[PDB]
Length: 311
Length: 302
Ligand SMILES: CC(=O)N[C@H]1[C@H](Oc2ccc([N+](=O)[O-])cc2)O[C@H](CO)[C@@H](O[C@@H]2O[C@@H](C)[C@@H](O)[C@@H](O)[C@@H]2O)[C@@H]1O[C@@H]1O[C@H](CO)[C@H](O)[C@H](O)[C@H]1O[C@@H]1O[C@@H](C)[C@@H](O)[C@@H](O)[C@@H]1O
Ligand SMILES: CC(=O)N[C@H]1[C@H](Oc2ccc([N+](=O)[O-])cc2)O[C@H](CO)[C@@H](O[C@@H]2O[C@@H](C)[C@@H](O)[C@@H](O)[C@@H]2O)[C@@H]1O[C@@H]1O[C@H](CO)[C@H](O)[C@H](O)[C@H]1O[C@@H]1O[C@@H](C)[C@@H](O)[C@@H](O)[C@@H]1O
Ligand code: NA
Ligand code: NA
Image (tube, rainbow over all chains, first blue to last red; front, side):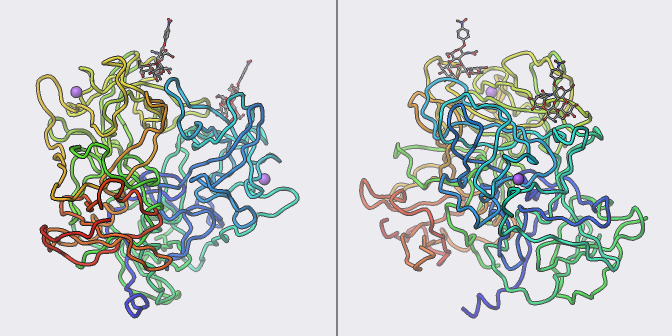
């Protein structure tokens, strides 16, 4: 319809501190730049074009995000993946089932239970561990491998990663949540991976939204999980499907108390934000978390942003 | 601002009492069922009620301080901000699962270590003297012999209440937020069956744990969480007694049934006799706002 092809672009009118991470369900706790200015990312969750096209394993909503489901035989180590709703995972079509975790460079410590409940007594929760850099980690091929033999009844199991730790191998290496796992095998490449996102350069830098995930690391600091977009942005775009009318959407991060612009950002159609750091050490991490991103105008990709923060 | 609801199939939307996909749309098994959920409560102009969060990020989490050797979790908001006593039933997003024991998993935050499993199991009964979230605290079943600090987590699975012994889980109910001395202030109000041929519509998702029926623990809620987020963002003024919705098959554009969305944040339909109701409909439909109507507008039976 005319209305559909002329639908004005909008973003959710909610403060950032109230919005959610798109790599796991949690409130956003900060904005950061990547420690390495050359950091390329290839997250498989939290990937959506601003006209509402989902990429990688990204779900439309948080209901499906960061869950794992599959069948496992008693005495086996192999979880044969399905979609979160129990339907078959069409392998080679996607890197993994929709919402499957994309936490690379760490060990996963999962909690799962047999579904649906068919019991009248007892604790149904089971602890399993998954390494992501071993030959058995092949979600693209339809399966992942637990560390230990699964001595519990054969069936359909659902759950999630509860906490993460430093990868078992190579021994001594740290968690690196900037990376995704290898979804494929030594024999087969993972098909339909969401593409990499490169630093824009020319004064601009990628903006990441972070939330702490349980577990230790070599730095005795929170495991901050960076993502490109709040989940509510993704849901909004999927619902709205507003046509992209320019190279980038200029956003102002506005203080709700004073109505003053705290920082200029560009939201690119590929589904990521940039800013111009106001010198070394400056950046969006210096801004309060109660601001609201407001859509100002479609702009050229060459449009220059006022630098944000203080060096 | 014109009123709209999210253009996303129902099966892709989320429960507003815990983060999970909606797996069904039902009427209450008891036609006289009154509900008083504290989460998933939002006026359709974007006004949150009870303990309802704007988004799923805050939903169904518990945070507080606990001392090594104590049984008491002194609650904060999920972001660590102080919780004000006597003001609300509980912190924003605090679970509202009544008539069950809670089996929680929590961890000390932020991480300040390079070693170890940080996860702790604790259990909470909701009908005991120590369950007083309105006063800012809940009591664990066992003494907490783990380091003092700021803990965050959620309910992992539920079971039949410890007392009275033998009683079953009933997720149509909420816990007792209040104390012996005072009732909880600012509870979201009860929602009563509308009568006049109409019936309340509930969105259901399964939650882990046993029960006396050896069946799934089904969690009913009044609105998908995405509807709440939408209303909070849009803040569209209510301009009729009810918003008339069509539940549309997006594959064909066929109208599968008429519903009313009331200003108080709940949906009704008219069942076409017994056996009929929204549970007969496929879950891939999208609700579409059609018109503001008066409360006397008669719905076509579903
Ligand atoms: C405190 C506890 O663990 N209670 C268990 C109970 O434990 C014992 C029974 C007898 C002895 N003994 O001879 O000395 C020692 C320990 O065992 C029964 C039977 O297995 C458990 O009840 C059953 O499982 C529950 C999950 C419910 O489905 C219940 O209906 C079943 O009968 C009992 O577990 C507790 O049951 C309570 C209701 O009666 C209530 O549901 C409570 O939350 C349950 O405790 C939880 O589950 C336990 C298995 C355990 O994990 C505990 O830490 C949890 O809090
Ligand atoms: C298999 C295991 O449990 N590995 C543990 C290791 O356990 C033992 C140490 C010594 C004995 N013994 O003398 O007989 C027996 C078992 O203990 C070390 C600490 O000394 C653990 O490493 C530390 O904790 C981890 C969570 C990491 O933070 C790590 O950096 C710390 O040094 C070790 O845990 C495993 O470490 C691996 C990296 O080296 C990897 O992170 C792996 O996932 C860890 O295993 C998990 O955590 C354990 C504590 C345990 O809960 C296990 O079930 C988990 O899979
Ligand atoms: Na692999
Ligand atoms: Na109480």
